[PDB]
Amino acid sequence: ALERTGGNKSKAARLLGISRRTLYR
Image (cartoon, rainbow, N blue to C red; front, side, top):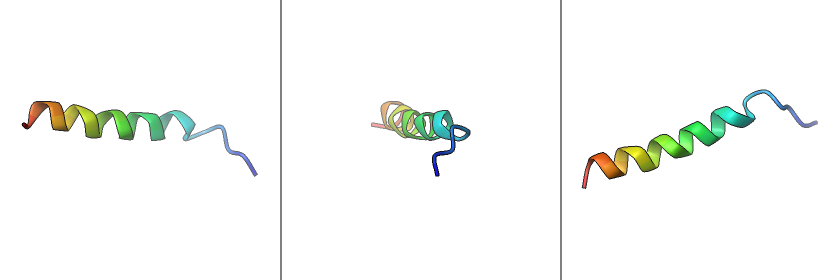
């Protein structure tokens, strides 16, 4: 079963991880 909901949420989670790394070197 494919759930459309949460699909974009996962993308944001990954984006945040990269964002955190940029802020903290």
